[PDB]
Amino acid sequence: SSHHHHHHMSGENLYFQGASAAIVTDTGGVDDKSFNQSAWEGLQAWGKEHNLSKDNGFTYFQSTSEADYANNLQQAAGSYNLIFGVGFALNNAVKDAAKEHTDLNYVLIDDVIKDQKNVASVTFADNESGYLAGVAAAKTTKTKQVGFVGGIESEVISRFEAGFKAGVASVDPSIKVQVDYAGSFGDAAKGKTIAAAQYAAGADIVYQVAGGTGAGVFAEAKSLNESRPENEKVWVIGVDRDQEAEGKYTSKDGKESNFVLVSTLKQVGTTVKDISNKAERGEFPGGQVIVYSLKDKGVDLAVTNLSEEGKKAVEDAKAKILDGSVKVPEK
Ligand SMILES: Nc1nc2c(ncn2[C@@H]2O[C@H](CO)[C@@H](O)[C@H]2O)c(=O)[nH]1
Ligand code: NI
Ligand code: NI
Ligand code: NI
């Protein structure tokens, strides 16, 4: 209201203490065009905003295996005071590291840690985005059969699967959803053989929810589509990022086209940048569980190459999820 006792201070003597933020990444890698890449793009954007460069204020530790999680988190604790575990698999390793270094701040993305003051947890309503992808798929199938390729069987991927199945059923319960898990988020070759089998059995759309494994699903669809006419093409649904650019191909008939129907979005990069800024300002949300959903645009659907009829079904289904009229199952 008033500040009568005051002293003039030079801007040269006032300074804001910066933080150093690192992500510890799973097998998928920061080049997975999806989940880990979104996180890494977010951290790079944050680095650029704070005048930093890789291994000088921000970095990523790629995990070779589960045994490398603890090694990478301990290496990170040498130089970084905000450490993100990217993926549900880092749950136990982040719990242990947070108990050893109570002075550092940790974030688990895609899972919850309870009762740890220096750990924040982030989850996404991927069931809600999955539902929208299902409505999209149900409005474009000609064969009335669609594929789902998961990475590792988990509460997280079951959220996508349940939402996707529910969204397909909301339009046409006649449609068959073939489900297959790769057992990995970093196995393109297994993604390719699963997609090959799903397409050969008469799926005309595959939704890939397996991070970097999904590069194989894109490779299979591209090979089938290059050896066919444009109007007989087979679709993939993108995940985490808008993957439209990965769908570029040329048909047997010489026509330039795109086989990405739609992508589910998961704003992991946005979350990494926002929490990094809060940690640097001394407002780290330790002990809290942050839930992103359709409402706050933490998840969404990019409607890329969907028919106008499909976009209407998606916009209508989105309204019903926001209003509460449709409750999307999580399992
Ligand atoms: N634990 C883990 N989950 C991943 C990874 N890549 C992708 N995912 C999950 O799979 C979904 C589809 O890529 C993402 O939204 C994440 O939930 C990874 O490397 N590790
Ligand atoms: Ni005042
Ligand atoms: Ni004074
Ligand atoms: Ni800074």
Image: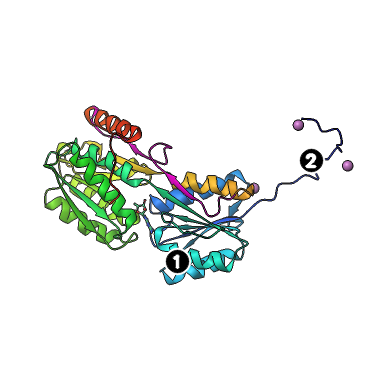
* Horizontal arrangement in the rendering, residue 239 relative to residue 72 (left or right): left
Circle count: 2
Q: Disc 2 vs disc 1: Cβ atoms closer than 8 Å?
A: no
**Front position in the image: 253 or 40:** 40
The reply to whether residue 122 is in sight is yes
160, above or below 325, in the image: below
Report x, y in % for residue 83. 54, 58
> What label sits on residue 147 in the rendered view?
none
64, above or below 249, in the image: below
Report x, y in % for residue 42. 50, 47
Nearer the viewer's eye, disc 2 or disc 1? Answer: 1
Which quarter of the image is occupied by the N terminus? top right
The reply to whether residue 248 is in sight is no
Based on the picture, tell me whether residue 318 belongs to the magenta stretch.
Answer: no
**Front position in the image: 322 or 189:** 322
Residue position for label 2: 11
**Front position in the image: 194 or 298:** 298
Please tell me whether mark 2 sits on a helix, a strand or a loop. Answer: loop
Residue extending furthest bottom?
Answer: 67
Kindly identify the residue that appears in the image at 16 percent across and 56 percent down: 197
Q: Which residues are magenta?
A: 284-308
The amino acid type found where label 1 is placed reads: Asn
How many other residues sit within 10 Å of disc 2, few (<14), some (14-19) or many (≥20)? few
Kindly identify the residue that appears in the image at 19 percent across and 35 percent down: 139
Report x, y in % for residue 7. 87, 38
Residue position for label 1: 92
Q: Main secondary structure of the magenta part?
A: loop
Circle nearer the N terminus (2, 1): 2
How many other residues sit within 10 Å of disc 1, few (<14), some (14-19) or many (≥20)? few
Q: Quadrant of residue 118?
A: bottom right
